[PDB]
Image (cartoon, coloured by chain):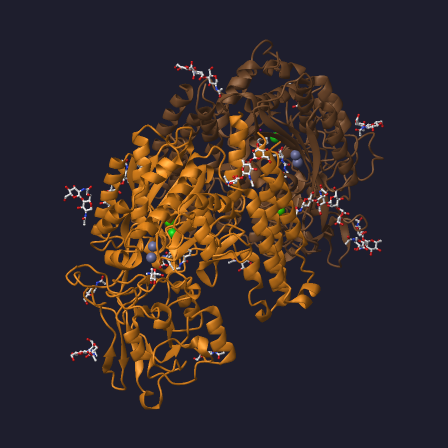
Chain colours: A orange, B brown
Amino acid sequence: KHNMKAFLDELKAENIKKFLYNFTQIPHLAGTEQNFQLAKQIQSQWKEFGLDSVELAHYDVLLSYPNKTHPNYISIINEDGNEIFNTSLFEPPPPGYENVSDIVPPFSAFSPQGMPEGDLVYVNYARTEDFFKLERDMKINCSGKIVIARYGKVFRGNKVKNAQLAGAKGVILYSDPADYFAPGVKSYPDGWNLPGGGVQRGNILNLNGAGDPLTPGYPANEYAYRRGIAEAVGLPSIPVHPIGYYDAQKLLEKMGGSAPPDSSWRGSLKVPYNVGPGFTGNFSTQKVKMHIHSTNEVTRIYNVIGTLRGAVEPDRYVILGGHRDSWVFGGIDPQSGAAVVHEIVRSFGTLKKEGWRPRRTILFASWDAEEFGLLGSTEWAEENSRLLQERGVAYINADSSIEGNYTLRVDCTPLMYSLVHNLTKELKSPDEGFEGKSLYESWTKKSPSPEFSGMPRISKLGSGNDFEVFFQRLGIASGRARYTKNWETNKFSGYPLYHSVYETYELVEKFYDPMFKYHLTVAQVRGGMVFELANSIVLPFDCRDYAVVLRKYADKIYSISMKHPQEMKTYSVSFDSLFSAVKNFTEIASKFSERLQDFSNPIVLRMMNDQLMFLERAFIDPLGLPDRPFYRHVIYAPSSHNKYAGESFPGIYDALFDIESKVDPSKAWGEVKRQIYVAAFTVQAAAETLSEVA
Amino acid sequence: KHNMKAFLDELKAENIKKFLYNFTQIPHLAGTEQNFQLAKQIQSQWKEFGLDSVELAHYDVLLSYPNKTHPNYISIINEDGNEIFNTSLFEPPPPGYENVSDIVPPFSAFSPQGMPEGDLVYVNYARTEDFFKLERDMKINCSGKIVIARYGKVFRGNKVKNAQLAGAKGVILYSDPADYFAPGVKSYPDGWNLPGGGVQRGNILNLNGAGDPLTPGYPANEYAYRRGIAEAVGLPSIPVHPIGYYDAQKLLEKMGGSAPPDSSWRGSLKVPYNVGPGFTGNFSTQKVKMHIHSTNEVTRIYNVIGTLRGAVEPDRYVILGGHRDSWVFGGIDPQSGAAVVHEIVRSFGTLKKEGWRPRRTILFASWDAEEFGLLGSTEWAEENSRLLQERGVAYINADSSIEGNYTLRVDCTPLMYSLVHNLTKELKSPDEGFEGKSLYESWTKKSPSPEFSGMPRISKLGSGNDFEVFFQRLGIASGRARYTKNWETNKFSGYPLYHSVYETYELVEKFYDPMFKYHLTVAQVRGGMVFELANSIVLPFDCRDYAVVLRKYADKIYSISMKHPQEMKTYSVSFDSLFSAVKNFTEIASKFSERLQDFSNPIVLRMMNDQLMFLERAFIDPLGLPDRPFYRHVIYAPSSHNKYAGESFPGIYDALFDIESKVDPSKAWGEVKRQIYVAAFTVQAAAETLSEVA
Ligand SMILES: *[C@@H]1O[C@H](CO)[C@@H](O[C@@H]2O[C@H](CO)[C@@H](O[C@@H]3O[C@H](CO)[C@@H](O)[C@H](O[C@H]4O[C@H](CO)[C@@H](O)[C@H](O)[C@@H]4O)[C@@H]3O)[C@H](O)[C@H]2NC(C)=O)[C@H](O)[C@H]1NC(C)=O
Ligand SMILES: *[C@@H]1O[C@H](CO)[C@@H](O[C@@H]2O[C@H](CO)[C@@H](O[C@@H]3O[C@H](CO)[C@@H](O)[C@H](O[C@H]4O[C@H](CO)[C@@H](O)[C@H](O)[C@@H]4O)[C@@H]3O)[C@H](O)[C@H]2NC(C)=O)[C@H](O)[C@H]1NC(C)=O
Ligand SMILES: *[C@@H]1O[C@H](CO)[C@@H](O[C@@H]2O[C@H](CO)[C@@H](O[C@@H]3O[C@H](CO)[C@@H](O)[C@H](O)[C@@H]3O)[C@H](O)[C@H]2NC(C)=O)[C@H](O)[C@H]1NC(C)=O
Ligand SMILES: *[C@@H]1O[C@H](CO)[C@@H](O[C@@H]2O[C@H](CO)[C@@H](O[C@@H]3O[C@H](CO)[C@@H](O)[C@H](O)[C@@H]3O)[C@H](O)[C@H]2NC(C)=O)[C@H](O)[C@H]1NC(C)=O
Ligand SMILES: O=C(O)CC[C@H](NC(=O)N[C@@H](CCCCNC(=O)c1ccc(I)cc1)C(=O)O)C(=O)O
Ligand SMILES: O=C(O)CC[C@H](NC(=O)N[C@@H](CCCCNC(=O)c1ccc(I)cc1)C(=O)O)C(=O)O
Ligand SMILES: *[C@@H]1O[C@H](CO)[C@@H](O[C@@H]2O[C@H](CO)[C@@H](O)[C@H](O)[C@H]2NC(C)=O)[C@H](O)[C@H]1NC(C)=O
Ligand SMILES: *[C@@H]1O[C@H](CO)[C@@H](O[C@@H]2O[C@H](CO)[C@@H](O)[C@H](O)[C@H]2NC(C)=O)[C@H](O)[C@H]1NC(C)=O
Ligand SMILES: *[C@@H]1O[C@H](CO)[C@@H](O[C@@H]2O[C@H](CO)[C@@H](O)[C@H](O)[C@H]2NC(C)=O)[C@H](O)[C@H]1NC(C)=O
Ligand SMILES: *[C@@H]1O[C@H](CO)[C@@H](O[C@@H]2O[C@H](CO)[C@@H](O)[C@H](O)[C@H]2NC(C)=O)[C@H](O)[C@H]1NC(C)=O
Ligand SMILES: *[C@@H]1O[C@H](CO)[C@@H](O)[C@H](O)[C@H]1NC(C)=O
Ligand SMILES: *[C@@H]1O[C@H](CO)[C@@H](O)[C@H](O)[C@H]1NC(C)=O
Ligand SMILES: *[C@@H]1O[C@H](CO)[C@@H](O)[C@H](O)[C@H]1NC(C)=O
Ligand SMILES: *[C@@H]1O[C@H](CO)[C@@H](O)[C@H](O)[C@H]1NC(C)=O
Ligand SMILES: *[C@@H]1O[C@H](CO)[C@@H](O)[C@H](O)[C@H]1NC(C)=O
Ligand SMILES: *[C@@H]1O[C@H](CO)[C@@H](O)[C@H](O)[C@H]1NC(C)=O
Ligand SMILES: [Ca+2]
Ligand SMILES: [Ca+2]
Ligand SMILES: [Cl-]
Ligand SMILES: [Cl-]
Ligand SMILES: [Zn+2]
Ligand SMILES: [Zn+2]
Ligand SMILES: [Zn+2]
Ligand SMILES: [Zn+2]
């Protein structure tokens, strides 16, 4: 038999281990030769594994690199302009590497050049609420200051945006042990914690879905017209650089001015966490000076695209994609995911060699330049947008397979909730203490739904990975799954060695998953999802699950608005249309479900498969959200305050956010009303796609 | 047998005549009770005729009406402010009407109110080139002047836009006998010419595809948020009013200043056609004063939507639509079209009652408020956009069936060229002298293709009718056909009694088509097209015909650019990518055609039917054209200088237009290059939708 069990049993922990080792011996930074060589290797192997075609799709996109002969660093400078302290020029390499070349030093990708000097202000996590506290409550002015912010809580590009709008002239990001050092575990190489010399790389763009900064809307192909740098999308206007906590301690220890406003502003270092501005009495005349010399450069990137043609519906695509480019060795991010995808391709190819083909076409992607802003996936989707929006069934992402060893973490469209529950009930739990129990059982026990008893937590999709263009721009049903930790307040912060030189094969093999059983479990979840999507006769989506969450999101946004009852009275702000639409959606979805259960007729089936495929597509508004034209889904967008987090009813959410501070309340509440209309209309229009067609 | 011949033979000239009479006894102005009553009648009859469902879809949109107790008119005013001449307050009603009430007086719909007074400048047809001649060559300044312009050549809303940008403070439109009085024929009621008291109504909006001015992007339903009037789309900023040639003679006879620059500026009245500004010596102190008091008002409109569910592909829609609202009696515009649609529905219903159903679903529409800016069709399409873009096969328009009695006129997508040629070869010519010959033969003889021997002329779709939203916004294959005159320079001007009170049943029955044989022929062309689209197993589109025209349009836009060889050198302006894309499109389209001819497999068929349906859809750019977000088709848009005319490669065309006058040539040619990239990319992406799917 060639069924899902055949597929799942063919997957081997030992193969994933071998591939992980193979993918993590040298750095694979986007735009470098080593990363092109790995692309060619994967293309060759996917051919050998049995795919019908495997091609490289290349693009020429804006990337950013430090200057090898003019290093970035930060100084404390004295009255005379003597640099009395300098931050490190590189992370101490881990054991046995120390002679690896081409390890890119820590830098903030896309920082402009500059040598700003000034007084420090400490801004906690540099969140919107942190700046509100500084400016509104503490009356501290960041204008012309260098801000220092700890990593964690929100995407770093939002920190930099917030610092810019506060008038900062530079930003220093650092890793506090409060957020990157788990109590009781040892620093790398003796455990999985971040050493004091470790630093988190990462880009600081605010692309809002655009892809390559120079070519928003269109692929960066050979004849592309590029914007000038001054009109590029998303580039920061002030210099930015990341440091480790040994260096941060040196910059923070002398800080003066106001005390931290409360304990949620204090990290774990032995410093006061004074907000500043500037240093205490004796050092009041010393300044901080940044030296940033990185350059932005148009550089070729390569996606590997493999096709397994469907036997029955070859013009319906189920896509499994994850990136290949890494900051350094990519031991977790992304190669723990890429190794899982490699083993999935191998298993599918095994079945194919025995004469099986999936019902629908499966596309496999190894994306490039994810680390520089989701560039590879976005440019490819821009190139192929018409094929994807008329043929795309679903997209399953496959970045890091593990960020912990505790339990499963899933974010996906409501359309896939039932599929995930059903699949996980059929898979074995890899967890100690749940031998012979299902993954569904361990996951539900360890990560209970906050709404429903006996169900696991599944979160909304946000952004910060390659599914963004598929879901938020194109409206293709998307999902992602991995193994995670038990550390709730660190949900968006990353594991301690995130984007550091210390993320190596050895990290994974010694400390995360020595048996590769969690990798195997994740391969079964991702692969199992792809198998069901590409093989089930009726697409495995339950429209009724969308109706349940739409009501939850409508209650939530109504509750936010109802914080302002006098204004809702004055401006006649009614949510009645949105609740009406959600009611209608619930009723129509129930009737559609009955018909779907009640029909030998392939035209009726496909008609109904097309209704299921196009339902996520119906939540797309071609006009986009306000000032964010590439975020087009009306139900979900990346939060405007934190790209990683999803926000529901984002148009209405942002119209309500901080509304009590707007100078013209009539205009502000008018825009809330406009967003309620758009949302109600889109929900009703999506409902109507599920009605009888004629 | 229930085949196309059965359908075509059931259509009767005598029924079309009876329906025309029935639809033209009282005015059916949008938003009035009489037009709602006619909607209800059509809904009832289409039910009786056999459709599966017939519903009214209503919307509340911005309309515009004169003030019944405060009439619009224009005066010549003297030194003291005595009004010494006044234009007419109404057109003399035709015989036997004179006691019809609710005939709306001539006005320009959506004019703002005002009583501007000033000196006249005569601007010929108020085209872009007419204003270029005035300002650049003759150095006449229109700022603060009232302009007087003859109707014809271009859409009146473009005239008003042009007058506004020239700084005019009011616009007077009039009908010159040069353009609205055919030599040798008598004025209504004794012939089909415009009397001197006749006046052409019409709106003067510049909506660029938006639909209701207050709700761009979204249907004007019961909970819609509306823009304030100041932010409405497309409204003119200066008062405008239309007059007949008796009145125009009075305003033009006293005109002084410069002589007309050449004979193409002179109409047929016995006046000099001096450009002005102002009157000759003796009258130099008299002025012209407008009095406009019309009001814009949100008003309910009603579309009738009938469905004939398909037997096999009910989720594929072929749409036959035309409007019902008229300025007055609508003898030609629109009821000559509406009567044809009514007879088509009757014939289809006849077949249905005998047990036949079309393969695909056919939707029939009687649109409202077409005359006020395509409002009914646009709002409906905004409401149903997701259904239309995933299910819409084709749209066939059905406004006026006749504007002459000479030969056929067709505008459609290249995808329908072969369908039109084939259908017309099977229909009888109604023409004298072509008894027993095909319509194809008479049409080709009377309207030869300018490119190809032995083929008839088929023009590009422009705008000015209800197909706009379907074609230019949504990318649904569209076409239109009617009987026309032999008067080439009057292509966009309208027949003489266009939008006048004199367009009556009697006009048609006495002077255009007493036997209703041209109406019947048009019913056979429109109905035959709908039948083939809704019934052919393989959709009747030939992608190779698009490849031929894309090459023609590429040669044309390249030729325009090559007027500027030095700039193409300086700025490295290459059309190579666009010709490459067109070459690829031609090659892939040829191979697709071979496969389409070479395949019992309904999935392969529908897969290939979907490739055919989505090919027009592939030319849509979701970002729209520059500053015209609702014109999204990259190959075709309404000309920026004349809404009625189609323009090919419009983005590149407008970037090139008058480029030698731009102040920053680097920037201007950069934008040409950007538009070449967008066009090349879109053509290649459309080509790729025709490749093998996997
Ligand atoms: C959820 O689905 C339901 C259908 O089950 C759908 O109900 C529709 O609601 C609209 C607006 O609420 C109804 O619109 C009415 O239509 C009638 C004609 O049928 C008009 O006469 C009404 O207008 C009068 O009353 C208005 C309200 O007081 C006045 O403002 C106006 O000036 C008129 O005097 C009104 O337009 C529509 O008929 C129903 N359709 C049904 C019941 O089938 C509802 O809209 C859906 N929700 C959403 C958000 O789409
Ligand atoms: C029409 O269809 C054809 C396919 O039949 C398609 O041809 C493609 O053209 C592109 C660009 O013209 C080719 O791109 C090249 O790809 C190779 C790798 O395969 C690269 O090495 C090339 O880059 C080098 O050379 C460039 C040009 O001198 C340099 O600018 C660059 O720095 C590199 O040194 C280059 O990107 C592509 O391979 C073909 N594909 C084929 C032949 O299958 C053509 O693009 C289509 N037309 C349109 C408008 O899409
Ligand atoms: C996840 O698994 C559940 C449980 O198996 C699936 O739901 C079940 O799906 C089947 C097939 O539609 C349903 O069977 C149907 O029952 C009705 C009688 O009410 C009958 O008319 C049909 O012919 C058919 O037998 C079954 O009721 C349903 N069970 C429940 C509790 O909903 C579900 O579809 C799976 N989700 C997927 C595949 O996304
Ligand atoms: C308009 O009418 C023309 C003429 O009938 C149609 O073109 C013809 O279409 C048929 C069906 O595809 C073609 O027949 C095929 O011929 C090939 C042999 O070359 C064979 O492999 C197929 O099995 C089939 O017999 C025919 O060649 C073709 N004629 C020409 C001159 O092109 C055309 O399709 C009609 N247009 C429509 C329906 O839009
Ligand atoms: O430019 C971008 O948009 C992102 C590029 C790059 N992306 C990442 O590094 N993404 C990492 C980020 C981890 C930290 C935040 N994590 C999450 O949001 C998250 C949420 C749910 C799951 I299941 C898995 C991860 C990842 O998704 O694994 C970056 O964040 O620097
Ligand atoms: O607001 C709008 O966009 C148009 C509203 C209203 N539309 C019309 O009156 N359309 C009339 C206009 C006739 C004059 C221009 N004619 C054409 O462009 C034309 C071209 C091809 C064919 I076949 C038939 C007619 C019509 O299409 O029959 C108007 O022009 O005032
Ligand atoms: C990763 O595995 C690949 C594939 O097994 C290795 O590449 C092969 O190496 C052998 C021996 O040098 C060559 O003969 C083949 O041409 C390579 N195959 C390819 C690239 O498809 C590669 O050596 C491994 N990398 C590491 C670091 O172990
Ligand atoms: C921090 O680094 C700077 C830059 O390399 C050092 O300052 C330089 O020192 C050399 C030799 O003393 C001088 O010739 C340069 O002119 C200095 N450059 C400057 C100030 O930009 C500085 O010594 C380092 N500080 C510490 C504490 O190591
Ligand atoms: C147009 O034709 C319609 C339908 O034949 C006429 O409306 C009918 O009139 C009869 C007699 O008054 C009524 O009993 C029916 O209820 C009407 N049917 C409808 C509206 O569906 C209408 O009278 C005709 N109009 C003109 C001007 O002749
Ligand atoms: C043009 O119409 C205007 C407006 O009705 C006429 O002017 C009015 O005439 C009456 C009676 O003579 C006066 O009471 C009003 O005050 C005038 N209103 C104005 C000037 O706005 C005028 O007589 C008409 N001219 C002609 C030639 O018929
Ligand atoms: C890097 O710095 C070196 C040495 O100071 C300089 O010569 C070169 O221009 C820089 N490289 C860049 C800007 O890419
Ligand atoms: C913040 O500080 C700068 C000092 O240059 C000043 O320009 C800005 O107005 C200040 N903001 C306020 C309103 O405190
Ligand atoms: C793996 O699981 C054990 C047992 O709970 C835990 O103590 C250890 O820290 C985990 N490793 C990681 C990297 O989370
Ligand atoms: C029309 O004019 C009359 C009489 O002058 C006036 O009372 C009324 O306000 C006007 N109607 C409108 C503006 O709709
Ligand atoms: C046209 O005339 C007006 C007179 O008020 C003037 O403001 C404008 O500059 C003139 N245009 C030119 C440049 O001749
Ligand atoms: C109808 O055809 C005749 C014969 O050519 C022509 O003279 C007459 O003017 C036509 N009627 C119209 C309205 O064009
Ligand atoms: Ca791009
Ligand atoms: Ca609208
Ligand atoms: Cl992931
Ligand atoms: Cl028409
Ligand atoms: Zn990653
Ligand atoms: Zn990463
Ligand atoms: Zn019309
Ligand atoms: Zn009209």
The outermost residue toward the top is B436
Residue A333 visible in the picture: yes
The outermost residue toward the right is B99
Relative to A176, B438 lies left or right = right
Q: Quadrant of residue B486?
A: top right
**Count of numbered circles on the image:** 0
Q: Quadrant of the C terminus of chain A?
A: top right
Q: In this rendered view, identify the residue nearer to me: A498 or B497.
A: A498
Q: Quadrant of ligand 13?
A: bottom left
- What residue do we see at 62% from left, 45% from top? A586
Q: Quadrant of the N terminus of chain A?
A: top left
The outermost residue toward the left is A99
- What residue do we see at 60% from left, 43% from top? A687
- What residue do we see at 44% from left, 19% from top? B453
- What residue do we see at 45% from left, 75% from top? A264
Question: How far across and down, in percent of the image, does residue A367 sit?
Answer: 32, 48
> In the rendered view, would you say B449 is above or below B247?
above
Q: In this rendered view, identify the residue nearer to me: A525 or A372.
A: A525
Residue B122 visible in the picture: no
> In the rendered view, would you say A52 is above or below A124?
above
Question: How far across and down, in percent of the image, does residue A139 sit?
Answer: 49, 81
Question: How far across and down, in percent of the image, does residue A680 sit?
Answer: 62, 50
Question: How far across and down, in percent of the image, does residue A628 sit?
Answer: 48, 55
